[PDB]
Image (cartoon, grey):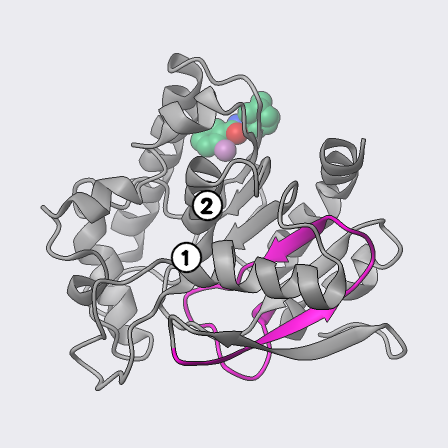
C-alpha cells in the first residue's frame, strides 16, 4: 500500500471549468512525458487506487516519466456524460474526457512543464476501455494505451446491462445519463472493439491484460460468477482476434494462467510495461 516516504509526490488542485469544481490530481514530476494512471469503478475522492494499493510512484521514480493520478470520478468511465446521474442527485455533469484531454493537460503544461502530447494512458477495470478510447480519439496525446481487465466490448450483448448494474452498485450512478439507452450512438462510440480500426489506423501501441477468475466491478448480486467469467473470456478472445483481423500488429497481450482481476496483478503489469513505455515515449 502506497509508496515509500520522501518521494516528490504533490497533491494538486486542477480547476475544471466543464465540471465547475477543482479535480484533485496526485503528481510526481519526472520528465516532459507522462503516464496517466486511471482508477477503477469504485474510484474515491481521497486517493487514486493506484496509490492506495501499489507502490506505483516508487516504481516509476527516476524512470524519465512523470506520473499523473487523477483522483475521483466513481463510475465515470472517464467519459463525457450526457447529463447528471439521475439516481443519486449528482449536481453536475461528469466531463472527464474534456478534463483529461483539454483542461488537465493545459494546466499541467503551464504549471508543471508536462507535454500535452506523447503520453501513455493506463487503465484498469472500468478505465481499461477508457484508456483505449482516449488513444483512439486523441492519438497525438496518447501514442500508448494499456487496458488491464478492461471492458472491451461495452456496447455488445449483455454488457450494457451488466455495466449499468455495476455503476448503480458503485455509488448509485445511472448508465443512461452517461451514454443513453444501449441503442444510443454513444455506446458504440466508446466501445474499444468497435474502435479497433482507429487503433489500427493510428498504429497505437496497446498493452492488454486479460485476467482470470472472480470478476472485478461487474454485474450485481443476481449474476452467477461463472456466467460473467465466461462472457469476459469470450469478449477478450474476440478483441484479440478482431484486432489481428483488422490489421492490428502493435499490441502486446498478456494472459498469465494465475492472473486475476486484482491490484497485485495490475501492478505486475505496470512494472512489466515500464521499459516498453520508456522506449515508445522517450526513444
Ligand atoms: Se489476452 C488473451 C485473452 C484470451 C485468449 C488469449 C489471450 C492472450 O493474450 N494469449 C497470449 C498467449 C501467448 C501468446 C500471446 C502472448 C501471451 C502468451 C498471451 C497471447
Distance from Cα at disc 1 to Cα at disc 2? 8 Å
Residue at the outermost front position: 110
Residue 125 seen in the current view: no
Screen quadrant of the C terminus: top right
Q: Which residue is mark 1?
A: 97
Q: Are marks 1 and 2 in contact (CB under 8 Å)?
A: yes
Disc 1 is placed on an element classified as helix
Quarter residue 91 falls in = bottom left
Q: Nearer the viewer, residue 251 or 14?
A: 14
Q: Residues within 10 Å of mark 1 (few under 14, many from 20)?
A: some
Q: Along the polypeptide, which appears first: circle 1 or circle 2? A: 1
* Residue 231 in the figure: left or right of residue 143: left
Q: Position of residue 249 (x, y in %)?
A: 54, 17
Query: Residue shown at 71%/59% (left/top)?
Result: 67
Q: Residues within 10 Å of mark 2 (few under 14, many from 20)?
A: many
Q: Which residue is mark 2?
A: 134
Q: Position of residue 87 (x, y in %)?
A: 17, 80
* Residue 139 in the figure: left or right of residue 160: right
Residue 274 seen in the current view: yes
Query: Residue shown at 71%/68% (left/top)?
Result: 111
Magenta region: which residues? 20-49
Is residue 18 a member of the stretch shown in magenta? no
Screen quadrant of the N terminus: bottom right
Q: Nearer the viewer, residue 91 or 39?
A: 91
230 up-or-down from 162: above or below: above
Quarter residue 181 falls in = bottom left
Is residue 44 a member of the stretch shown in magenta? yes
Query: Residue shown at 29%/50% (left/top)?
Result: 228
Amino acid at each position: 500500500m502506497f509508496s515509500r516516504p520522501g518521494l516528490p509526490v504533490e497533491y494538486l488542485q486542477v480547476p475544471s471549468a466543464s465540471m465547475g469544481r477543482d479535480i484533485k490530481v496526485q503528481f510526481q514530476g519526472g520528465g516532459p512525458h507522462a503516464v496517466y494512471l486511471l482508477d477503477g469503478l469504485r474510484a474515491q475522492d481521497d486517493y487514486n487506487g493506484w496509490d492506495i494499493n501499489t507502490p506505483a510512484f516508487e516504481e516509476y521514480y527516476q524512470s524519465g516519466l512523470s506520473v499523473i493520478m487523477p483522483v475521483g470520478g466513481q463510475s465515470s468511465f472517464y467519459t463525457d456524460w450526457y447529463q447528471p446521474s439521475q439516481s443519486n442527485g449528482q449536481n453536475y455533469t461528469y466531463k472527464w474526457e474534456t478534463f483529461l484531454t483539454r483542461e488537465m493537460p493545459a494546466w499541467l503544461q503551464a504549471n508543471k512543464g508536462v507535454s500535452p502530447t506523447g503520453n501513455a494512458a493506463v487503465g484498469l477495470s472500468m478505465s481499461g476501455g477508457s484508456a483505449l478510447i482516449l488513444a483512439a480519439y486523441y492519438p497525438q496525446q496518447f501514442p500508448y494505451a494499456a487496458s488491464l481487465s478492461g471492458f472491451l466490448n461495452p456496447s455488445e450483448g449483455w454488457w450494457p446491462t451488466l455495466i449499468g448494474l455495476a455503476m448503480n452498485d458503485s455509488g448509485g450512478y445511472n448508465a443512461n445519463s452517461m451514454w443513453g439507452p444501449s441503442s444510443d450512438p454513444a455506446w458504440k462510440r466508446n466501445d474499444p472493439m468497435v474502435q479497433i480500426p482507429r487503433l489500427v489506423a493510428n498504429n497505437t501501441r496497446i498493452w492488454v491484460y486479460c485476467g482470470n477468475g472472480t470478476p472485478s466491478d461487474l454485474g450485481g448480486d443476481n449474476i452467477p460468477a461463472k456466467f460473467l467469467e465466461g462472457l469476459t473470456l469470450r469478449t477478450n478472445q474476440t478483441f484479440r482476434d478482431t484486432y489481428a483481423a483488422d490489421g492490428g500488429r502493435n499490441g502486446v497481450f498478456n494472459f498469465p494462467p494465475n492472473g486475476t482481476h486484482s491490484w497485485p496483478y495490475w501492478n505486475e503489469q505496470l512494472v512489466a510495461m515500464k521499459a516498453d513505455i520508456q522506449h515508445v515515449l522517450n526513444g
